[PDB]
Image (cartoon, coloured by chain):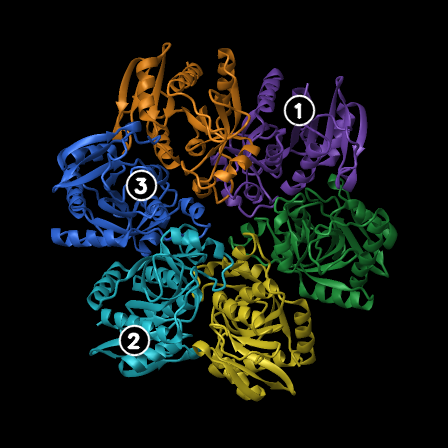
Chain colours: A purple, B orange, C blue, D green, E cyan, F yellow
Amino acid sequence: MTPHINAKIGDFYPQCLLCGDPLRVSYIAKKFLQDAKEITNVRNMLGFSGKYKGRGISLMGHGMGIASCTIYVTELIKTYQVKELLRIGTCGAISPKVGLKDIIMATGASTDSKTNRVRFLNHDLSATPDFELSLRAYQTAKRLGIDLKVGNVFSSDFFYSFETHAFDLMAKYNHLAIEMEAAGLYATAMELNAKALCLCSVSDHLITKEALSPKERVESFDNMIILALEMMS
Amino acid sequence: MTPHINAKIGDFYPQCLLCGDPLRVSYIAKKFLQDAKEITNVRNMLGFSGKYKGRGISLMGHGMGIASCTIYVTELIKTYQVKELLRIGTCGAISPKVGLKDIIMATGASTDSKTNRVRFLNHDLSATPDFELSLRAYQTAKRLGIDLKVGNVFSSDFFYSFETHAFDLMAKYNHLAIEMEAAGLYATAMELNAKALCLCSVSDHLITKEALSPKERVESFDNMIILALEMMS
Amino acid sequence: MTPHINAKIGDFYPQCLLCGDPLRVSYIAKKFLQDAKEITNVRNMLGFSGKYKGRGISLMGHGMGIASCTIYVTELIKTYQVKELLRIGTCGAISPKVGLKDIIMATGASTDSKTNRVRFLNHDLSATPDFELSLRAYQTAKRLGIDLKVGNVFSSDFFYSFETHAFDLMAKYNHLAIEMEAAGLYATAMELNAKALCLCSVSDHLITKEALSPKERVESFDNMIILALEMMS
Amino acid sequence: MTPHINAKIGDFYPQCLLCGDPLRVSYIAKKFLQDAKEITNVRNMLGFSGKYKGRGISLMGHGMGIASCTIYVTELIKTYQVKELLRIGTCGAISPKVGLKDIIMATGASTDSKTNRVRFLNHDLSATPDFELSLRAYQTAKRLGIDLKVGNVFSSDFFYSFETHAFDLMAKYNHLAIEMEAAGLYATAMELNAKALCLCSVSDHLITKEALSPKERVESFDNMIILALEMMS
Amino acid sequence: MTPHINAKIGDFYPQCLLCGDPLRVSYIAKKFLQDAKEITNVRNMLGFSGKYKGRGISLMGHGMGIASCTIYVTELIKTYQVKELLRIGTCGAISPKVGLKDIIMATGASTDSKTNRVRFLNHDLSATPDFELSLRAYQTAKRLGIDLKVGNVFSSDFFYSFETHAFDLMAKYNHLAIEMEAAGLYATAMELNAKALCLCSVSDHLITKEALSPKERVESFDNMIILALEMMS
Amino acid sequence: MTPHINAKIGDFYPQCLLCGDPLRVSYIAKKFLQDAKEITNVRNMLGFSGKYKGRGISLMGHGMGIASCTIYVTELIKTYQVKELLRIGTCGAISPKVGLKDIIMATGASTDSKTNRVRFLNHDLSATPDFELSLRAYQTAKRLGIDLKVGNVFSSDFFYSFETHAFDLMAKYNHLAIEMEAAGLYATAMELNAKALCLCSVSDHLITKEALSPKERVESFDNMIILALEMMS
């Protein structure tokens, strides 16, 4: 149907889970979904539709960078009628409020992209999640004894940043971690009146140079895929 | 003590409700607080300290526009150790999703001001409110039966806009109404590690040209006043 | 009548003195004008009409920052048919060419605001006063024995600057002091074919830190008030 | 070895062909290289190494958008010692100077991204390819008798444009087509002193609205795969 | 001595007249000066020193555009000790307040150049003349029977504008004409603590499309030449 | 005919050499062409027509800076039907890849000017020459035994930079030298669908502070003149 998804009109559940990594897309389908079927794979970017504890969920990969995410989020919304889009991934912590393992809920995604200025009269679009997915996230985490942590992220166009001198100022302004797609997600979902949210797990801490060795990696991660699949039940 | 605030240290409770109009601050103090006491009056910009149901609460006017708001919040936080800033005021609605009498919770404050680009590396700061404050508002609105509309707001440098043709584009991106201070409030609280939220009563709707009577005003502004006093007592 | 002025049409004389502080306006009306009457008091922003040397003068407060100033002078010109606007105020000197108690005539008002790019094609609007008003100021000052310092000011959206390191560069480019409204006053009167001028009294020096005593401030501001009333009569 | 490439230092040859679609990297590998070996598959993005008419060629996919391309090009150059990067892809045409089937060499890559302004002092970086690569591309296509259309492309952050009205002005200034990567490839190559060039095949024509049929995509594509492989040998 | 001026040190008087056109400079020197001496001729950009009513006056051409003017003005001040610079030239009127043969005094010089954002912190530099030179111009015009038309000019990088639809807005904001150097002359004189002014002869009206004959051009410019030489003697 | 060229219709051959310095133009005319005739001299900006190997070639001065170059180039193309414009000039090297006497071929002109943002949607116009001309230049340089340096230049609005600290970043991004017209030439040629190239002779090195003698300057320029005349033959 779409230039980047050849799934079938209705193959998606109205509530989709999102990663940049199509590998962890399937990792969630395998380890977490019953009735798991692969619905899309153009450019090897994969999505799945299954059921989590009797309730049907879709999964979908969005690649890396705001433009990439914008392409897939736009198509999930305008063609496949997706309505709620949760995004989950890792991030680089920059705030002394976050330690590794932590899960961040992004109540706002700042950015160095020009996309929002192109979208929004060259003014300052404050790209924000949808509210009633956010309180769902805080209630389900307290429900779970997860100390969900809430603040802004900075969505950058640069994985290898040319402005590492500025992280302290970003963290000063309640940016807990840096990721690369939430601003495009939040903005696209704003443009199209859909509901979106983004969570991230602190894998690396860019200030304390600390990191998670591959052990607790796909164990810290999993502790928030259920977070997401829970919230979404 | 500061060039813009007249009060001794300790005169301000760590919780403070904010309005642009200092005569609404004065109206709130007399009609809703016990033992109210005018603690500042520089440039006729009034502030009060009193109690609402046993709980100590402060009130402060902040003038019109981001620059004015910013001066007053900076001095509240850094001299008078105010920790929670809740702003209530009116707004011109631009979104079909709301109408007169509605109370908006601003989960993002977009802007045409340059101040956040000055603050934040010439990038896009998503100015946002403190999440736990945004939670107590949702909880208190529900307890009180208020249908709280939740979305973004646009803080303009212009009361008389030169971009009225753009109100639709803003409404499309889930900007419910226009005011002039939220983005500066949210950015100053982010800079100084304090908690802030902005609530807005729809007094006029700039697209539907509907206004309301100069007495349903004080009554629906009253609603918001009780909602705010309640969520911090 | 307007949302921010509740004076009747015709209550304002065609020449108007402005200050940021309404208690300053009130001070001028009681001490220096004859037969002054309060004509507006919305949001505690007082305005007055009275007589000086047989001639009708109006006073009006405009609050703090470009956005607030812009509201009041837009309304004064467009609704109350004010033709000439003289703003007096204090300022923080940044240049070695001025000292305490100097009066600066602002023949250019630079800014970190975005309002003039929004107004003016996103180009650089050189915000300037009316030349005939500035000529009348220089002639009245000469008659009074006042050595007027003439140069640019910098109108900032920030009272508490994040760019203090730049004050020397501003001084280099003939910015004698910093204040927060001139560029908006000048742009609005340009927009609306009205005549405006800004005079600033040097009460503090931001570089050398010298300040005026409380008595010296009153005396200094009085010398500027006499200058202003004399050049409007 | 890197966060996004799984190969080891040694597995990439100095000369690498680039595509956005990793399935297209495999098509080329299976049909054109002997000894084809898959060397990386992080996030399911596939790189290959093999031989073409005796000489060793490498292949790597880079995803969609300037940000995603930059992550991979940076890693290929800095970690895997790639030195020539030839990019081949599709493009939507916007100019009357090109029809379908045609191959465009991008002697420059304009863009609506802010990445080059972040990289290059908020000025205008003219992102261009290495001249030696483009000289071979023209000589090789001349030997194969392929009519090479040479001019600028426009690299955008947007697959689904918000500025369709602008395509005519882009084509007037000698932009033959729009894609989403060339500017980031050229600017990363410039940054890290590597040689880069972008060729792209006209699969769509956004103005005349006519596209290539299913069989016709891979047809004209091949003719350009050979041009690329021929010029690396 | 400088790369663009080969006059001996001391060849320039401290007061210098400027035109874009070196042949206009040549014309002034032959027709109006006593003992005119050509002192520099690099790139055919002529300059002269001579006498007017027994007082030394220098002349210098500066070519077309902010960048050309900035070069010559920078060298005249820093190397040749020029202290006052008076620019006289033609312009394309855009305001209904001026007609053919008017002389405009530019109390401000707006621009579509980025030069002042580069000079001045990416903020808005309000480029203005020296007030005393303005005053001396006004008093000399009055003495000679010349009614100066006083307001802003817009200094553009473009002779052949791509924004002719904006002229009405420029005129609305008190821009009386368009030329191509004043903003550079003023910013450079401000940078270097020198005294500068720009005077413009209305030879063409861009709105009405009326234009002076070749004779009427000579006669009109001569009257402005006498204004200039008189205000310097 | 135009306000800046007084050549009669058809005086210009469709191939034209361009220099900033009109006396450099006059020099080429007497030393390097046969039957040379001066065809324009407005504002002392000389232009010539003549023959090299019996083929007609025209020569035109274009002053200093983008705004000035843009004027003469627009009129050459639009009014005099010039189809091929070749700019030869000097520049100041900033890269260790080049030294004195080297001839640079600008395949890209970055800039700090705002002209291209004004022309091109406020985006990044990557300003480039006509490939065919650049190829012809490379073939002729090899045919002449000339070691052509190839890369970008940076076209500044400033001869006296305020950003000398940033010359290594530019050199890092393969800007070999700094001049002041190339991006204006390239953009105007793109605008009006004509063919242009820029060649520089390195006369000063802004890093190492090397510079050429008065003599070494004309001997190396004569090399560049021969290259230019040969590739038009």
**Label 2's element?**
strand
Q: Residues within 10 Å of mark 1 (few under 14, many from 20)?
A: many
Q: Pick the quarter of the image with the N terminus of chain B.
A: top left
Q: Nearer the viewer, residue A179 or D149?
A: D149
Q: Which mark is residue E58?
A: 2
Instruction: Say which of marks 3 and 2 sits in front.
Output: 3
The answer to whether the residue labelled 2 contacts the one labelled 1, judged by CB atoms less than 8 Å apart, is no
Query: Which residue type does callout 2 highlight?
Result: Ser
Q: Which mark is residue C77?
A: 3
Residue A203 in the image: above or below residue E199: above
For mark 3, name the chain: C
Q: Residues within 10 Å of mark 2 (few under 14, many from 20)?
A: many
Question: Between marks 2 and 1, how big is the CA–CA gap?
Answer: 78 Å
Residue wearing tag 1: A228
Q: Residues within 10 Å of mark 3 (few under 14, many from 20)?
A: many
Question: Residue A230 at x, y = what percent?
Answer: 67, 20
- Callout 3 and callout 2 share a chain: no
